[PDB]
Image (cartoon, grey):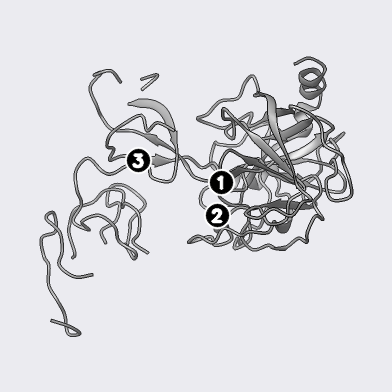
């Protein structure tokens, strides 16, 4: 995350690390034995890590749970990214304390101008590299579906939605993919893509979680 | 994972944000065996290194400060002794390479 600040040992209890040797993606636990993440973050052999502060160090408040099964999404298409979402089932289901908690699904896509909380373990240097040990945090408003397109000519869709600062310098970045973009108890966004990181007229882009509300009920009901 | 190609020049980087990046390879090519699907080889490699180039660049290889020209078709133009593809090597006032060639610059050195 570029431009953010340190969150604080578990303050984002629903935040998880998608791991397979090393941390490659985000993930916000939506409940007991499940995890919501990105489409492109899909791989074979996920090990979900919950309740972490320093990812490169054990602190007995972590829970390593492999991935019983890792679903993806129908329309998901790699080229345009439209429909960027994956669903992960835990071989088990954690304890759910203060540190490790569940976020909550939306009811109605939040409007623009809304300050949301975006977080991850990605890069904190736009032009460069400086991947942090502790989880970083960023407050950011939603841009109008109007302005989103205004920056990414013919690339947005009924799902992806920008968020961030048009002037830039503060945004989500490499490492953060599959992260949570919360706005008042509601898991409204999922880290998806963007040209570079935090660069004027090149805000980030996170998929609309509200438009997969049903999709999930089903996918969890079954599978 | 398994890099679906030995070398690649036109290396595109997905806009996506995992760690490491996920890249795609363009390259003209011939349907040799052309990977796991072809139109170019539409297979995405996900890793730190997107591979070496197929044909070297004046910059030799790496360059920490490589000027550029995003648009078409300048696409940029970035030590000690220069490299085999260089062509105008020269020291300078301080102690005892600029090339007209274009194309997507490779990584940096530091």
* Residue position for label 1: A194
What residue is shown at x 60% (from left), y 25% (from top)?
Answer: A76
Can see residue B39? Answer: no
Proximity of marks 2 and 1: CB atoms separated by less than 8 Å: yes
* Residue position for label 2: A197
Mark 1 surroundings: few (<14), some (14-19) or many (≥20) residues within 10 A? many
User: In 3D space, how far apart are the residues under numbered discs 3 and 2 (Cα atoms)?
Assistant: 19 Å
Quick check: do tags 3 and 1 share a chain?
A: no
Quick one: which residue is furthest to the top in this view? Answer: A222
Mark 2 surroundings: few (<14), some (14-19) or many (≥20) residues within 10 A? many
SS for dot 1: loop
Instruction: Identify the mark at residue B11; answer none if there is no mark.
Output: 3
Front residue of this view, candidates A33 and B63: A33
Chain bearing tag 1 is A
Residue A105 position within the rendered picture, expressed as x and y whole percent measured from the top left: 84, 35
Q: In which quarter of the image is the N terminus of chain A?
A: bottom right
A121 relative to B74 in the view: left or right: right
Chain bearing tag 3 is B
Q: In which quarter of the image is residue A42?
A: top right
């Amino acid at each position: 995350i570029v431009g953010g600040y340190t969150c604080g040992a578990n303050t984002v209890p629903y935040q998880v690390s998608l791991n397979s040797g090393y941390h490659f993606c985000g993930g916000s636990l939506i409940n007991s034995q499940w995890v919501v993440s990105a489409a492109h973050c899909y791989k074979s052999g996920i090990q979900v890590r919950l309740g972490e502060d320093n990812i490169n160090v054990v602190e007995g408040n972590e829970q390593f749970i492999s991935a019983s099964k890792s679903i993806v999404h129908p329309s998901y298409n790699s080229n345009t990214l439209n429909n960027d979402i994956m669903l992960i089932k835990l071989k088990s289901a954690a304890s759910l304390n203060s540190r490790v908690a569940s976020i909550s699904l939306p009811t109605s896509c939040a409007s623009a101008g809304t300050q949301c909380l975006i977080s991850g373990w990605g890069n904190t240097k736009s032009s460069g590299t400086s991947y942090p040990d502790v989880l970083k945090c960023l407050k950011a408003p939603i841009l109008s579906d109007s302005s989103c397109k205004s920056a990414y000519p013919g690339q947005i869709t009924s799902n992806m939605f920008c968020a961030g600062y048009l002037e830039g310098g503060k945004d989500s970045c490499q490492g953060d993919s599959g992260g949570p973009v919360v706005c008042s108890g509601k898991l409204q966004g999922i880290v998806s893509w963007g040209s570079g990181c935090a660069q004027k007229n090149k805000p980030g882009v996170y998929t609309k979680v509200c438009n997969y509300v049903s999709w999930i009920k089903q996918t969890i009901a079954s599978n | 994972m398994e890099r679906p190609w030995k070398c690649c020049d036109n290396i595109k980087r997905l806009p996506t944000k995992p760690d490491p990046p996920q890249w795609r390879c363009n390259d003209e090519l011939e349907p040799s065996q052309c990977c796991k699907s072809c139109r170019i080889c539409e297979d995405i490699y996900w890793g730190a290194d997107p591979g070496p180039f197929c044909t070297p660049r004046p910059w030799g290889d790496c360059c920490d400060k490589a000027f550029c020209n995003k648009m078409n078709p300048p696409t940029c133009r970035c030590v000690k002794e220069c490299a085999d593809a260089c062509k105008d090597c020269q020291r300078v006032e301080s102690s005892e390479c600029k090339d007209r060639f274009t194309g997507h610059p490779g990584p940096v050195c530091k």
